[PDB]
Amino acid sequence: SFLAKVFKGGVIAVYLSVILVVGRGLVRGIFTTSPSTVMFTELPNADHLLKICLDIYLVREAKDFMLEQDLFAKLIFLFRSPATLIEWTRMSKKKQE
Amino acid sequence: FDFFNMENFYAHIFNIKCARQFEAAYPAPRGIPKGKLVKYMMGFPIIIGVVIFIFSPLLLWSLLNQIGTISMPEKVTLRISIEGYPPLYEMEAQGSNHDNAELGMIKPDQLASLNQALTDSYTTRDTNSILRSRMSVSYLKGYTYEDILIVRFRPESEIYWPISQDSRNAMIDKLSRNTSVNFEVSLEFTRPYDPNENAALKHSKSWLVPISLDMTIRAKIQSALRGDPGHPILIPQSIPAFIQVPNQGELTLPTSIGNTIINDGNPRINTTGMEKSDEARAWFDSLTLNLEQGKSQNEKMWIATSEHPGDQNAKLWIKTANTTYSGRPYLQVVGFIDRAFPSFLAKVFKGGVIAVYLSVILVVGRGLVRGIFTTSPSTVMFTELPNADHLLKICLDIYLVREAKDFMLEQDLFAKLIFLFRSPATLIEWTRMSKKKQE
Amino acid sequence: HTDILCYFFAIMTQVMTGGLITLPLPLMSLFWGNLSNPRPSKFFWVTMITYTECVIVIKFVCQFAFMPYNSITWRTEHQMDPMSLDKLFGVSQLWDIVLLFSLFFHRYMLRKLGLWKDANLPIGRFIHQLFHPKFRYIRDLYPIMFGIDVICFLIMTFGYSAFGESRIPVTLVVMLVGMTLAIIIDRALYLRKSVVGKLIYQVLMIAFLHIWVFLVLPNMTRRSAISNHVAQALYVIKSCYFLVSAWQIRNGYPELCIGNLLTHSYGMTNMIAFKVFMNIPFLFELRTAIDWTWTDTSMPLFDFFNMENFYAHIFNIKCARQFEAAYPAPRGIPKGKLVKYMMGFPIIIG
Amino acid sequence: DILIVRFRPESEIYWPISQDSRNAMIDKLSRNTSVNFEVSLEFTRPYDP
Amino acid sequence: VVIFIFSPLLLWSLLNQIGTISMPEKVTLRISIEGYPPLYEMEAQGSNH
């Protein structure tokens, strides 16, 4: 009578139900990468977008909400057209320069 | 991670190309509407599956409830005693055939007579009598003649009185003072084994009638207990006449019959503003006890006798038997037996069940089903491709190079694939359908 | 619209007593008046008047004392059974304000006759109602029917203890909910210009409802009519559905411009409506499958679902833009202290 | 796992019956009613905390 | 991955742990006529076996 046994079949169901969600979702996401999230996750040099991301905060500190609003559309457009994103995140050249 | 990305890309390309080939392997007139058959050969199935998926965990619940039944008791016993002492009178009735006089069923004649008696106790003017008769008849008619038992105990106790001299002296000396002394009436029913759940269900109930503080009453009780010839110990409002036996727990009194008796017919007292403890016990029967003793002090038995409250033979009472062995009336108790056990898993807050019952219905549809039927507004540039035969070439060629070493070509051809999933213009250019047909 | 009032009061006076003596009143009223013409020819009204006078007379006679419905025996014995003889036979047995619905119906029936005096004054029946109505009135009342059906499904659900004899959820509730969902589907199929289909539909459902409410449910739930205070509401709502369906049947179908009754006004109410429509599970997909199975398309089902998703997305985007534009807002001044505490504060607490 | 229980032939206590119950026994057996015997056996385990 | 797959079985196998109990120490037998005090009652006790 140690906890007896609730329909072992039902136990196995849950025992698998958990094995499912975890792998079919979390583990999948962790090991692997969606065919859509390739243009964003890998970028040769992500130093130009960080400049804007810091600059908007810097402007925010010193008021000037006009520049604060005019520089958010500039960022929102970079995630719209992949050609400009690829152009801007390309690796820098001073080394052979 | 690049390995996993490449394998995912290969799987996607393989699936797309193969789906295109399978679709092309079956020509189909570009125009004529879907045939009536085809539609009913595809649409119909879905609807039925969705409906059964929605309404299945209710069907299984309805099959799972399955309110069970149990058999009626086979053992009854009653014990009358003074508080904190061995019982004065103990009597039991056994049997399982339900035909003997000790434990017998109820004939339809008695049930019909009692039902007729219930209705005529009212008076034309008073509406409270109307409501009381309505409630009492509604309660009585809820049990068929197969769910009512008539228990009959013998007046004489089955065994002698097993008391010592010192305990009797303690009884007398306790009664001498101005302390509080109580009586005790206990009744219990026993069920049959019931294998499925283990154990024999037992129902017991105990009443307590306090003794009056007047010195004369205590003197009479002391004279009776000492063993004097004529002293009929009297206890009022002790044993009921109707008892409801639930499926589990303590015995329950039928309250509607009490309201029908203490109010209709001839009202009995209830005019002194009695407390609620005796308000619900005002329709009980009274008991009297005598001591027979005999030749010696070893033989000491107690004989009990019941008296009805209010007016006797008011047609609301079932006639008793005059016994056979030696002649005095049986002690009769009528029991309404309830045999509708629903403890099958009982019920955890049905609301909580419904919550989970819906919680599951939610995740499945709001996620899996959605993904399966329908398509994200983002995954259109990839899922449908007019001709996915050029990407499969690269996907196979990278493996072919991998087999023959040459890791330089192996690495220089992975960026070529990674760039095709970056710029949609080149993807659309490359996956466009081929031209040799009109070429 | 006094005739609609007469039908409504006939339904009320039938549900008030729940017998079969009054049953010919609504049965005949529906079958004849709601299917004949805009004007039942002024002879049907005479028949209704005569039957109402007769029923008033007999139910006044049956409310006497020498006859066996006394308070001594019969009332007490038959108080609990739902389908014995006197409960079953209309008015034959108390009532505080007694029955006023029949009297009010009679008064309004004579008011209708007086209004008829004030103004203006069976193969042929089907031929007139179906083939020669002539002035087709082009209207489209289906959303009202859907609202009525939604109101009834929840009353079948939220109220479940009455339909069953913690108690048991009962196996019959499942049959009722499945059957009601099937009727909801059947409405959708018959929304494709099938007048004779709708006529057979209405006859079948009126017959089924009338027999089931008064002759089967009392035997199942062990609750007599009048005492069941929720089934009467279902009867009334279904009767309103029957009246509007009869109105639709008598007139001609409209062009039926395909589209939800949510894509006409681009307001804030449509947002809540569409959001609850697409938020509850197993509804969008069910509606899409029901639509595609019984409408003339050329694309397979997956393209149908993709198109519906695209339409929903476009509708939501455009409507959100309009709602945002409907409230001008100074481009510059920072968020007011109130607004912030009228929005931020709530979230934190939740 | 096998036990050999041995009860004494003689009963441990006397017969605690009254005259009236014995008369009831005899009179019930006199008629053509149905009368049954009864043999009951029970084992008791240790506390098991 | 292997331990994640095969752990909730290992924990089940450790969790079962079929227990044991000790043998009875009290027995009794009662022979009677139906609906009457017992004719013969006898019990046997002991724990040393």
Image (tube, helix red, strand yellow):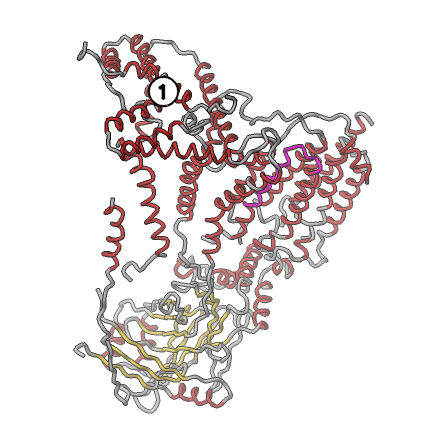
C335 versus B289 height, above or below = above
Closer-to-camera residue (B321/B180): B321
Q: Amino acid at mark 1?
A: Ser
Residue E36: quarter of image: bottom left
Is residue C162 visible from the viewing direction of this image? Answer: no
Identify the residue at horizontal 63%, vertical 49% (top origin): C212
The magenta span reads C178-196
Image spot of residue C121 (x, y percent): 83, 27
Is residue C305 visible from the viewing direction of this image? Answer: yes
* Element under disc 1: loop
B271 versus A78 height, above or below = below
Identify the residue at horizontal 53%, vertical 62% (top origin): B142
A54 versus C208 height, above or below = above
Image spot of residue B279 (x, y percent): 43, 60
Look at the image and tell me in which quarter the N terminus of chain B lies: top left
C210 versus C314 height, above or below = below
Image spot of residue C266 (x, y percent): 51, 20
Closer-to-camera residue (B340/C260): C260
Residue B115: quarter of image: bottom right
Image spot of residue C87 (x, y percent): 65, 54
Classified by dominant secondary structure, the portion drawn in magenta counts as helix
Closer-to-camera residue (C216/B98): C216
Q: Is residue B99 left or right of residue C142?
A: left
Identify the residue at horizontal 26%, vertical 50% (top origin): E6
Which residue carries the number 1 mark? B423
